[PDB]
Image (spheres, coloured by chain):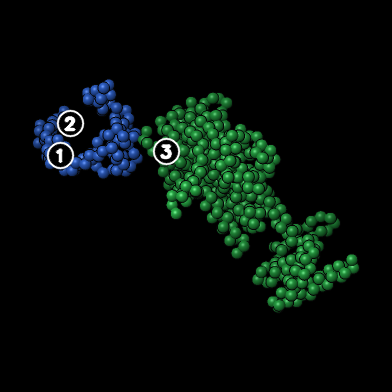
Chain colours: A green, B blue
């Protein structure tokens, strides 16, 4: 029903719910579904449980439609969240963090370094993004001693002394220059929203400044694990947004829509399959060919196989009259004659069986299964390990079936 | 006294010798509450001529920036990193020495 949809949009980030990672979030919500179970009542219930209150109040916008037409006319710990949600408190007590760990972060000259709550799995999601906002500056107004970015998960004193090491892919605010560089960007100062994101399709790390996309800083970073990372000198503080509480500034949703449309453009723009011919001695053997499936629209084999599957599904479901109408329409339209004869034999056999007293759903289920199997096994793009991986951009149930 | 057509006269002790210095202002453009522009605040001609010796006159066109305590501070660290403003910067220690020499600076910072 709509209440589950309202709760899952009120709990999780919106851009994460349009990726193939949304299955795991749906499973996580439905496992702990007893806690939760016209959107004003749902928002009030979520605030009573607590999703819209801290201490800076988590406000919400609610329009007034009737008046407008009148005058004119930790729960995330309980659920099992596996993505970063807060900064981690260092055991040496060198930082000041708030209760929620995102609202304030101030060091208590050497850098104070810290990382996030959890790491980012390589084979699970498509695009990750989070923002920071500089609240105070301890030099010039547009010069802050903050380094923000990502860190490779397999030197900490080197990070405290210098600001970064060889495993940090980040953006430095004291000179406007990336860590392991080049003319990329400019330094940021007070009241500046700096966003960091990673793209797992082509595998690149990008940064944004006040809603403007600043380009790709690092490239060819696939099959790796990263953690958010920040380094601050004492005197300046940041506010972090991982997307759970408030809305982003960037419009990352448009970025994701552009990449999904590019992937869909790249992909989508005999007549009996028989048994699997590569079973010998009970095991799968690799044929020494280039492809195993050789169906195409331009040769007419794909519509013929689709028509055979449609006829078999219609007969199997007890819709023999509809199959007869489909066969008549195929006769009216006219290796199609062999398809006509095979279909006619199928209705004759079904009529004989009915007088004496599937494959499509397998295609759908196998399509979903091979999309997920491609996702979780880190397949290469086309030939090289640097090509984009378009299967990461496909949500099969939300973009094709519905 | 910082009108466009205004003349100033004095000396200058260089090494141990004395020179006569004349300043003629040309354009005076002093900002207000908000200023994120690098247009020069003052402009003029400065001419130095010999007084003790027979040194010939050397006259130059100069430009100048005032110190407002919002953007252009006393120390050359709040001044932005620009190719036009990079010739006014020395060191915070040198700035502190050359400003603490004046008594009005001290009377400003002790109120």
Q: Nearer the viewer, mark 3 or mark 2?
A: 3
Q: Are marks 1 and 2 on the same chain?
A: yes
- Reading the image, the residue beneath label 1 is B3
Q: Residue at x 48, y 28 (%)?
A: A107
- Reading the image, the residue beneath label 3 is A191
In x, y percent, where is residue B11?
Answer: 13, 32
Element type where label 3 sits in the image: loop
In x, y percent, where is residue A252?
Answer: 52, 48
The image quadrant that residue A296 belongs to is bottom right
Q: Is residue B99 above or below residue A291?
A: above
Q: Nearer the viewer, mark 3 or mark 1?
A: 3
The residue lying furthest to the right in this view is A356
In x, y percent, where is residue A370?
Answer: 70, 54
Q: Are marks 3 and 1 on the same chain?
A: no
Q: Which one is in front, A152 or A329? A: A329
Instruction: Tell me: A15 left or right of B64.
Output: right
Q: CA distance from mark 1 to mark 2?
A: 28 Å
Residue B95 appears in the picture as rendered: yes
Quarter of the figure that contains the C terminus of chain A: bottom right
């Amino acid at each position: 029903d709509d209440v589950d949809r309202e709760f899952i949009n009120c709990l999780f980030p919106s851009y994460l719910l349009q990726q193939p990672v949304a299955y795991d979030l749906w499973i996580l919500y439905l496992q702990h579904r007893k806690l939760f179970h016209t959107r004003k009542e749902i928002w009030s219930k979520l605030m009573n449980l607590g999703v819209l209150g801290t201490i800076q109040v988590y406000k919400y916008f609610y329009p007034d439609v009737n008046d407008f037409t009148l005058r004119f006319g930790d729960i995330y710990k309980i659920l099992g969240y596996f993505l970063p949600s807060r900064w981690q408190a260092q055991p040496n007590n060198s930082l000041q963090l708030s209760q929620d760990g995102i609202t304030h972060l101030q060091p208590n000259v050497d850098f104070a370094v810290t990382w996030a709550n959890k790491s980012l799995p390589d084979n699970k999601l498509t695009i990750f993004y989070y923002e920071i906002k500089v609240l105070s500056v301890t030099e010039s107004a547009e010069n802050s001693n903050i380094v923000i970015g990502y860190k490779l998960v397999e030197s900490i004193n080197k990070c405290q002394k210098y600001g970064f090491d060889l495993n940090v892919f980040g953006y430095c605010g004291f000179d406007g220059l990336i860590t392991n560089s080049k003319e990329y960007a400019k330094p940021f100062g007070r009241d500046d929203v700096i966003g960091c994101g990673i793209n797992f399709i082509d595998g690149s790390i990008f940064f944004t400044k006040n809603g403007i996309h600043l380009g790709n800083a690092f490239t060819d970073l696939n099959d790796l694990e990263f953690v958010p990372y920040v380094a601050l000198r004492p005197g300046n503080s940041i506010k972090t947004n991982f997307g759970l509480n408030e809305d982003f500034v960037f419009d990352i949703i448009g970025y994701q829509d552009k990449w999904k449309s590019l992937a869909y453009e790249h992909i989508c723009r005999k007549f009996l399959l028989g048994e699997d011919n590569r079973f010998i001695d009970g095991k799968l053997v690799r044929p020494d060919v280039n492809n195993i499936n050789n169906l195409s629209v331009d040769d007419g084999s794909l519509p013929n196989t689709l028509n055979v599957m449609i006829n078999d599904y219609l007969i199997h479901e007890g819709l023999v009259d509809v199959a007869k109408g489909f066969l008549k329409d195929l006769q009216k339209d006219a290796e199609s004659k062999d398809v006509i004869r095979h279909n006619e034999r199928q209705i004759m056999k079904e009529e004989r069986m009915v007088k004496i007293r599937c494959a499509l759903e397998n295609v759908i289920s196998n399509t979903r299964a091979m999309l997920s199997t491609l996702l979780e096994y880190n397949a290469f793009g086309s030939t090289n390990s640097s090509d984009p991986r378009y299967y990461k951009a496909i949500n099969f149930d939300e973009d094709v079936l519905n | 006294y910082l009108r466009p057509r205004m003349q100033f006269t004095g000396y200058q002790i260089s090494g141990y010798k004395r020179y006569q210095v004349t300043v003629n202002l040309k354009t005076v453009d002093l900002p207000k509450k908000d200023c994120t522009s690098l247009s020069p605040h003052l402009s003029g001609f400065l001419s130095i001529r010999g007084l003790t010796n027979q040194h010939p006159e050397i006259s130059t066109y100069f430009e100048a920036y005032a110190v407002n305590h919002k953007e252009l501070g006393f120390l050359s660290s709040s001044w932005k990193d620009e190719p036009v403003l990079n010739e006014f910067k020395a060191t915070d220690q040198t700035d502190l020495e050359h400003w603490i020499n004046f008594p009005s600076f001290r009377q400003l910072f002790l109120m």
